[PDB]
Image (tube, rainbow, N blue to C red; front, side, top):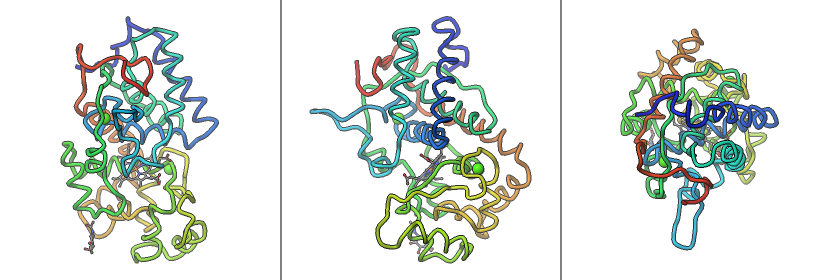
Length: 294
Ligand code: HEM
Ligand SMILES: *[C@@H]1O[C@H](CO)[C@@H](O)[C@H](O)[C@H]1NC(C)=O
Ligand SMILES: [Ca+2]
Ligand SMILES: [Ca+2]
């Protein structure tokens, strides 16, 4: 029931407003564009794209923020707050947090050089959150190719699309604690690549130490992610699992040689993710504050 022109009459300038907030936020911090995109992913994979990941914990409620894959990982909440506030003065109670999260993800990719896609709008916000689902549904970086396939299959994604979506790691950064085991106890990685990574990612401590996902173009949305994979320069265990004599090898090679096919396929995959269990019609609500239920 989602449409790109959903806010055409209700709030004509909503999209422009969102693009502007994102553009400056990602200009001050390139990484922000990656945080926001990921934020949308963490929203959609846990009980639909309903902004459930934005609800703060309270005296009688526990959201998704403390979930294993969320705690100390996901960021961007502040940026979303100001985007919401601006749109609220523009047209009170029209634009939902769920849609904002979907647009921000898109504008961020574009700000970082990626190809834009038509975002479908019309999602409503939830009154609930699932800590448990956040823990189980979201993939872990130590998963093997089969496990990743299962994880995406549960949401209706195919192996190819999994490869397509992992491309999102063409921008952003990961904490040392997320790849430490790889650069030390793994062999399928360029020795020199590992060596340097061992420097700013001690086997003992320094968990917080961040390192780029795409060493070639850390903050530019392109197909370089796949090029790294071929040259065994993947950051996470889950990253190299796509190019290691397995089924996904061909797709990785296809993407590394043709950037356009990646750009196109990614947009389509994002639109698909944006359609994960949405609340529409009159169900849910248009939160005035993305951190709390009305
Ligand atoms: C294929 C399985 C995937 C796994 C196992 C996974 C896991 C991770 C982990 C461990 C981090 C870093 C967390 C931290 O250290 O704080 C991360 C970052 C990131 N991921 Fe994924 N991810 C996957 C899929 C995706 C998808 C499909 C998207 C969404 C389109 C995405 C977008 C990003 C972005 C852009 C970052 C960087 C965030 C930032 O710099 O703030 N990831 N991912
Ligand atoms: C991943 O694969 C390795 C080698 O088959 C295996 O030892 C390990 O237990 C697997 N872990 C997961 C989470 O699948
Ligand atoms: Ca959700
Ligand atoms: Ca890149």
